[PDB]
Image (cartoon, coloured by chain):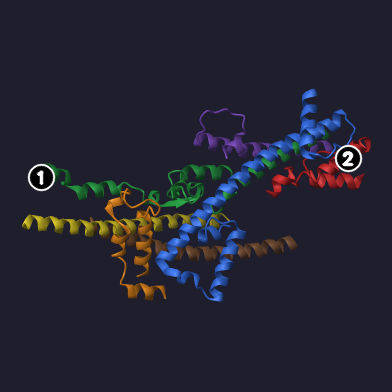
Amino acid sequence: LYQLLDGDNTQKLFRTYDGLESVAQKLSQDIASMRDQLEVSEQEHSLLLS
Amino acid sequence: IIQESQRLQDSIQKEVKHFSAICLPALLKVSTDGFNLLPSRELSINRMSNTHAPYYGIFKGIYESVRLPLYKAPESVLSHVADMKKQLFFLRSQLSSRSEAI
Amino acid sequence: MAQTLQYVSSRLSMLQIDEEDLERNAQFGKVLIELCPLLGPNGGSANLNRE
Amino acid sequence: EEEVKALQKQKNLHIRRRNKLQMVESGNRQMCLKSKDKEEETGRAFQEVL
Amino acid sequence: MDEKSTKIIMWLKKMFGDKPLPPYEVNTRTMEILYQLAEWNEARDKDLSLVTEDLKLKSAEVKAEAKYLQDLLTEGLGPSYTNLSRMGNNYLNQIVDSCLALELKNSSLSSYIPA
Amino acid sequence: GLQQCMLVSECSRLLTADSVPPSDSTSILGLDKQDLLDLLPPNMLVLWVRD
Amino acid sequence: QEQIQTAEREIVGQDLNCERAQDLCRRSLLLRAFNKKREEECEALCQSNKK
């Protein structure tokens, strides 16, 4: 689950459970932030069209 | 006789006090490969779903973070996170397309 | 060409492919059609999807 | 008008399911109050064994 | 440019195996599309491999727990719990198949109702 | 009768390291599966509960 | 839908109280078996003291 979330990129000698929850929260925030950026891009495109 | 009698003094009350501190589910052993008896509490299905596991509070925070409902199968967790990563990659492509079109 | 684009976009929905990209690169369009059965509908390898 | 009909049907379904959940919850809460009396009875039987 | 080109040629060799690589028009745009496809496939194949190996582990754990529950019910209730009527066994199968369709943790109303 | 049969079978499984040879396994409270079988209802009551 | 999710949380909270009552029943059965075994050992020591 940690490998699925953070990839192989972090050579963290120790994986923690707080670290697992943090990377899970980050995936959820990255999806939310990309939806918000897409919605801003839709508004900009709608304003250009108008 | 005095020495061995002193060892056995309050024996029942010593054992009962130690027994009171034990987690009964930790005694329940299961065999996955026929040879290795593991405590049922060490099975990943139970660590992730059992309300009496010490890790239950941590896996609850992970499920809320990934928006996985608590009624779902614990084996569905990695497949759900893999589909969330697929969704993130799709939204990245979509934003790149739309920014190039603008 | 439109049918080729529609087939590739249905199986590889993550690929931004324009109709101009296939018109200028007709042999590249054949490579994408040959890749479409080797890639599952999810972008993962067809063998890994069977397993 | 189809959407209003669909939402009316969904509203009626949620009203019925909520009433059922409240019946289950009320039955369960009455079972749980009695299961607390049971936890006190078994807690007394456990003190008797001690 | 040379690193992306080597990664694409390596990936295409891995995907086509012993099939001869079809000739194609090698330009900036076709190499960019193939590079994105190769990165996406490598990432997806890693994620799929991790899921497949966890499903193998979970299959062994669920089998171990199934045996525990079967033997517990056999010791407590005797072989009587397996001797259900044709309708009792149809009702049992419908609860099981409904809970499998919904991917439930267990057969409780607390899991079925939210799902 | 049903509650007692289930409790004895559950507790019997908490004591049984079924695969460890009997000479070397310290049991909890020094209890064996036999010590719990004595707390089971009369065999007539067990058969009647099962039926 | 908020009313439904609130009542669903209350149902899941009740399942947790039933497992505690069962843990007390298992402990009380094991401690009864233990008391019986310690009465038998006490009866053996009483016979040795009479001698």
Q: Colour of chain A?
A: purple
From the rendered image, report the letter of the chain displayed in orange.
Answer: F
The amino acid sitting under disc 2 is Gly
Reading the image, the residue beneath label 2 is: C29
Please provide percent x and percent y for residue B25: 40, 51
From the rendered image, report the letter of the chain displayed in brown.
Answer: D
Question: Where the C terminus of chain G falls, by quadrant?
Answer: bottom left
Q: Residue at x 70, y 62 (%)?
A: D6
Q: Colour of chain G?
A: yellow
Please state if F28 lies on the left or on the right of E20 as rendered.
Answer: left
Label of residue B1 in the image: 1
The amino acid sitting under disc 1 is Ile
From the rendered image, report the letter of the chain displayed in green.
Answer: B
Please state if E55 lies on the left or on the right of C29 as rendered.
Answer: left
Please provide percent x and percent y for residue C33: 85, 44
**Residue that sits furthest to the left in the current view:** G51
What kind of element bears circle 1?
A: loop
